[PDB]
Structures are given as C-alpha cells and as structure tokens.
Amino acid sequence: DPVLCFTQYEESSGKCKGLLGGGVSVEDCCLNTAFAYQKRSGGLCQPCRSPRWSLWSTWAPCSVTCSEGSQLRYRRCVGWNGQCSGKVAPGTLEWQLQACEDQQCCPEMGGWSGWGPWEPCSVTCSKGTRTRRRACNHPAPKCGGHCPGQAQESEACDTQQVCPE
Amino acid sequence: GVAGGWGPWGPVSPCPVTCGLGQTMEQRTCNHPVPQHGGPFCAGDATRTHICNTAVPCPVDGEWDSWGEWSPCIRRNMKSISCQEIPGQQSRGRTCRGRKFDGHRCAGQQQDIRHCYSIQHCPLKGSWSEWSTWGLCMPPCGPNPTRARQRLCTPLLPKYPPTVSMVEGQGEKNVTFWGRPLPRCEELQGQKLVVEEKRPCLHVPACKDPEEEELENLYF
Ligand SMILES: *[C@@H]1O[C@H](CO[C@H]2O[C@@H](C)[C@@H](O)[C@@H](O)[C@@H]2O)[C@@H](O[C@@H]2O[C@H](CO)[C@@H](O)[C@H](O)[C@H]2NC(C)=O)[C@H](O)[C@H]1NC(C)=O
Ligand SMILES: *[C@@H]1O[C@@H](C)[C@@H](O)[C@@H](O[C@@H]2O[C@H](CO)[C@@H](O)[C@H](O)[C@H]2O)[C@@H]1O
Ligand SMILES: *[C@@H]1O[C@@H](C)[C@@H](O)[C@@H](O[C@@H]2O[C@H](CO)[C@@H](O)[C@H](O)[C@H]2O)[C@@H]1O
Ligand SMILES: *[C@@H]1O[C@@H](C)[C@@H](O)[C@@H](O[C@@H]2O[C@H](CO)[C@@H](O)[C@H](O)[C@H]2O)[C@@H]1O
Ligand SMILES: *[C@H]1O[C@H](CO)[C@@H](O)[C@H](O)[C@@H]1O
Ligand SMILES: *[C@H]1O[C@H](CO)[C@@H](O)[C@H](O)[C@@H]1O
Ligand SMILES: *[C@H]1O[C@H](CO)[C@@H](O)[C@H](O)[C@@H]1O
Ligand SMILES: *[C@H]1O[C@H](CO)[C@@H](O)[C@H](O)[C@@H]1O
Ligand SMILES: *[C@H]1O[C@H](CO)[C@@H](O)[C@H](O)[C@@H]1O
Ligand SMILES: *[C@H]1O[C@H](CO)[C@@H](O)[C@H](O)[C@@H]1O
Ligand SMILES: *[C@H]1O[C@H](CO)[C@@H](O)[C@H](O)[C@@H]1O
Ligand SMILES: *[C@H]1O[C@H](CO)[C@@H](O)[C@H](O)[C@@H]1O
Ligand SMILES: *[C@H]1O[C@H](CO)[C@@H](O)[C@H](O)[C@@H]1O
Ligand SMILES: *[C@H]1O[C@H](CO)[C@@H](O)[C@H](O)[C@@H]1O
Ligand SMILES: *[C@H]1O[C@H](CO)[C@@H](O)[C@H](O)[C@@H]1O
Ligand SMILES: *[C@H]1O[C@H](CO)[C@@H](O)[C@H](O)[C@@H]1O
Image (cartoon, rainbow over all chains, first blue to last red; front, side, top):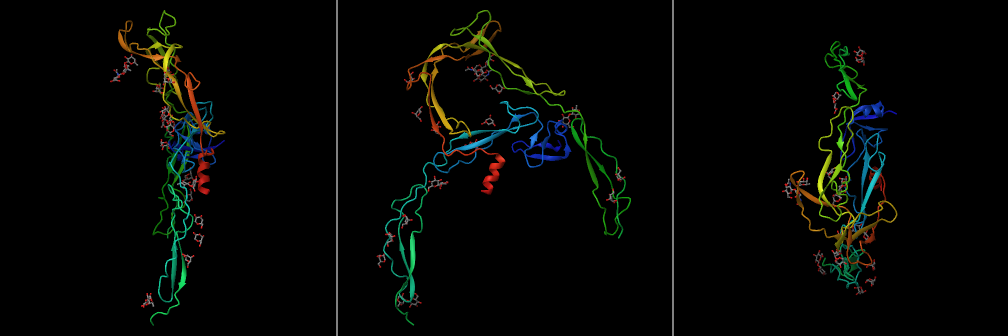
C-alpha cells in the first residue's frame, strides 16, 4: 500500500519533516532507516528505525486546581517492522498517572452580613442617588472565595427641594 | 510582446544516494524562445523532480541492549559461598542488536565482571526503613487507581572487607553484595517483611489519544 515518504523524522515532537513524495511502498521508503512515513496525511508519523519507546511527555495539567488531583503522561511506541519492549506493536500508548496538588487550600465563599444603614441622598436638591453597603465577613472567605453578588446597592432618592434658581 | 517558451531539458542528475530512495531533477531554460519587453512569460515549471529507488537497504549501526541480570556469585572449586567471607566473581551480558547491512559493530566490552560476596537466602538482622516515596497511581487508566508507599525491613549487611587483593588477578578489586537475604526484625503492625498502605487517587482523568485530547479540550 503506497504511503507518503518523508526524508527526516523530528524527534521530541513526532512530526514528519521534509517530504520526498508519495506513491511508494512502506518497504521501499524504509530502506533508509533515517526516513519516516505518514499515510493518508491525517497524522501518525512513524520513523523507519526499528521500534523503540519514545520519551515520556510532560505531565498534563492537574485534573483539578483544588486539593489532591491526578495528572497523566504518555509514551508511544515509534518505528516500523518489529516490536517495542513489552511485546508491544508500533502505535500503542502507555500511561503513568500521578497524584498532583497545585495549591493547599481551596476557595470557600462567604456569606453576606446584615445590611448597613441607608446612606443619605447624594444631593440636597432635585434628585440624586442613595447607596447602602455591606461586608463579606459573615463568614469571611478563606483562600480565594468571594461572596455571591455585589457588596453595595444604589437607588434614586428625591429630596423634594428645588435648587437656588 | 514576444512569447517565450521552453528549450530542451538538460541532463537528469544521477541518483544521489547509494541506499534506499533518492531524488533527481532536470533543469531547463527559457533560452531558445525568449520573452521580450515584459509581455507574456514561459508557462510551466523550470524544474521537474522524480524519485529514484535503489533497491538496497541502508546500513544500520547496532546499538547496545541493556545489561542483563548479574549471574550467581560463586567461586571456582568451592560450590555455594553463601553467608561466608568468600569473594567470588559474577558476570553480566549485553547483546549487540540491530546491526544489519554492513553497519558498524557495537563498540565496547560485551561482558562485565566484578567481584562479589553472596548473601543469597542468608538470615540477617534488620531494621525498619522510613516511609518510601508515594508511588504512581496504578492501574493507570484502569478502574480505581491507588497509590502505595511502604516501609520494609532493610538488612544490616555484615562488616566484610570491601577491598580485597585477588591472588589470581594480582589486583586490589572492589567487592559488592548480591542476593536476596531473609531479614529478621520485630513486626510492624502484624507484618515481618513489608508493611504498605494504599490511598486512592482523586479526580482521575480519562485516557485518550494525545492528538484527540488536544482536539477535545480545544473544542470543549
Ligand atoms: C569500589 O571501587 C571502585 C573502583 O575499583 C573497582 O571497581 C569495581 C567495579 C571492579 O571493576 C574492580 O576491578 C575495580 O578495581 C571505586 O571507584 C572510585 O571511586 C572514587 C570515589 O568514589 C573515585 O574518586 C575514583 O575515581 C573511582 N575510580 C577508581 C578507578 O578509583 C568505588 O568508589 C569503590 N566503592 C566503594 C563503596 O568503596
Ligand atoms: C481552579 O482554581 C481554584 C482556585 C478553584 O477556583 C477551582 O474552582 C472550584 O471552586 C469550588 C469552590 O466554589 C470548589 O468546590 C471546586 O473543587 C473547584 O473545582 C478551579 O477549578
Ligand atoms: C444642598 O442644598 C441645595 C438647596 C443646594 O444649595 C445644593 O447646592 C447646589 O448643588 C448643585 C449641584 O449639586 C449646584 O448646581 C448648585 O450650584 C448648588 O447651589 C446643596 O448641596
Ligand atoms: C553508499 O553505499 C551504501 C552501501 C552505504 O554505505 C551508503 O551510506 C549511506 O549514505 C546515505 C546518504 O547518501 C545516508 O543517508 C546514510 O546514513 C548512509 O548509511 C553510501 O552512501
Ligand atoms: C520516561 O521515564 C524515565 C524518565 O522519567 C526514562 O525512562 C525516560 O526518559 C522515559 O521517557
Ligand atoms: C512533570 O514533573 C516535573 C515537574 O513536576 C517535570 O519533569 C515536568 O514538568 C513533568 O511534566
Ligand atoms: C448574600 O446575598 C444573598 C442573600 O441576600 C445570597 O446570595 C447569599 O446568602 C449571600 O451571602
Ligand atoms: C438586607 O436587605 C433585606 C432586608 O431589608 C434582606 O435581604 C436582608 O436582611 C439583608 O441583610
Ligand atoms: C434604609 O431604609 C429603611 C429606613 O428608611 C430601613 O429599612 C433601614 O434603616 C435602611 O437602612
Ligand atoms: C514549456 O513547457 C511545456 C512543454 O514542455 C509547455 O507548457 C510550453 O510549451 C512551455 O513553453
Ligand atoms: C524535456 O522533456 C521531454 C523530453 O524528455 C520533452 O517534453 C522536451 O524535450 C522537454 O524539453
Ligand atoms: C547497563 O548498565 C547501566 C545500568 O545499570 C547503564 O549504563 C545501561 O543501562 C547499561 O545497559
Ligand atoms: C545485578 O545487581 C543488582 C541485583 O543485586 C541489580 O542492580 C541488577 O539486578 C543487576 O543485574
Ligand atoms: C522495626 O525496626 C526497628 C527495630 O529493628 C524499629 O524501628 C521498630 O521496632 C520497627 O518495629
Ligand atoms: C512516615 O510518615 C511520617 C512522614 O509522613 C514520619 O513519621 C516518617 O517519615 C515515616 O517514615
Ligand atoms: C507522598 O505524598 C507527599 C507528596 O505527594 C509527600 O508527603 C511525600 O513525598 C510522600 O512520599
């Protein structure tokens, strides 16, 4: 079955670099074990060297930003005509799962306290704004929490007073 | 307004490689009919390429396989030297693998010898080690992964000479310890040899293809 035959295999990232062309058999392309191949061009670049396990990828981000979690890393068997260590065929994957911990504590939101008294009106003639405010300290949040909503409300007030002309 | 066209194709290059596949190319010029004053140009490509196939494989230099298992520590004409001050010699083996098609041979000693004592199945006093480093979450991707750390009863190796004058070799060679002893020690929570403890791993991620996991998080 014909395949695209590439002249160099980039280690560390698995890409097929330097296209020599297509419409040639896998056996002919891999006469030079320094070459690499890709079929249908969807992906999966396999070097023509004998099969050997690749390098462990970098640890994936922890599954949660909170408390103990779990993170993976992969390793692919890359090559052609043979097997990797483990009676494994080329293309298979092997995983290692590890317990991770980005931060110790975790955001626990708090609760609003009682409403403060209404402040006076923002103006002494015509119409203005009235504001009341509360605190996020019943209970206070730990780590990165915050109370749900706003810490202050505003509303219009009418003084019933005309301004000096 | 003069129309250019191509001239004869030149000589094709020979197959630049001696193994596997290579590439050749022919060079033509737009010299016989020339494009004057900038009107039309030469249509096409001034270079064709073609693959040439040498039917002979490339050399592949053999690489060293990993070291084998240390052989049993013995001494000539004395049978088992276990739990005794008798230095022996054990050997290890490598295999040169992958050499094909006149490739270079592996470079180095395929064997490795070292002097040793034998503590195979010897009863030794022991002491409980501290808590080892938390291992990997196993089985990875399987149902309910769990970690494991452990304290094991480490043997107290006997104070034997680590530097011995070999009379047959006339050298002062180092001597290390080989074998699985039987460590004696007070029990640690109903156990005499090893006591471990497991803890489940939390929020396990599913195992998908590294391309597929990349395209899944990008799409959400
Ligand atoms: C054990 O001895 C080695 C070197 O001596 C021997 O090694 C054996 C494996 C065997 O092949 C035998 O024939 C050979 O004679 C010591 O290596 C030395 O270590 C010191 C300090 O660690 C270094 O400064 C030296 O460069 C290094 N090499 C030499 C040639 O001296 C090794 O330290 C020793 N181990 C112990 C625990 O004593
Ligand atoms: C990663 O960063 C952390 C700081 C949190 O913001 C995580 O969000 C989630 O927060 C709630 C608390 O409201 C916890 O119960 C969750 O466990 C945590 O996932 C965020 O993912
Ligand atoms: C409170 O009492 C009112 C009767 C006014 O005297 C107010 O002063 C007025 O404020 C407006 C804008 O706030 C200004 O345009 C006027 O010039 C000023 O007379 C007072 O604050
Ligand atoms: C021609 O004869 C062969 C028997 C090999 O010795 C060839 O060596 C190979 O040459 C190509 C480039 O021309 C390299 O890609 C290979 O790494 C090399 O083994 C020789 O050229
Ligand atoms: C991953 O694991 C170890 C390093 O952590 C090595 O055996 C190798 O680098 C592998 O890719
Ligand atoms: C995970 O582990 C260490 C960092 O904790 C590094 O080897 C690397 O970042 C890997 O992804
Ligand atoms: C304060 O605001 C409302 C109650 O008024 C709720 O979202 C919650 O109790 C918060 O603490
Ligand atoms: C202030 O607003 C109302 C009462 O006016 C309630 O949602 C609550 O008591 C809050 O503290
Ligand atoms: C403002 O509104 C009334 C009094 O006008 C009360 O609910 C409270 O004092 C609030 O602060
Ligand atoms: C040169 O190349 C081809 C003929 O080989 C045509 O496209 C055209 O004649 C051009 O001049
Ligand atoms: C080169 O290629 C072919 C001959 O191989 C012809 O189309 C023509 O001679 C061109 O110059
Ligand atoms: C054997 O010796 C060491 C490991 O003990 C390494 O140099 C290498 O893995 C070799 O095969
Ligand atoms: C021989 O030495 C020890 C076992 O005593 C290990 O490093 C390994 O098994 C090697 O083959
Ligand atoms: C076993 O090992 C030593 C004694 O040999 C102590 O750490 C303790 O008694 C443990 O049970
Ligand atoms: C393991 O447990 C704790 C540390 O987690 C200590 O008591 C000691 O290091 C033991 O080995
Ligand atoms: C496992 O747990 C933590 C690290 O995750 C440490 O207490 C220690 O490394 C232990 O082996």
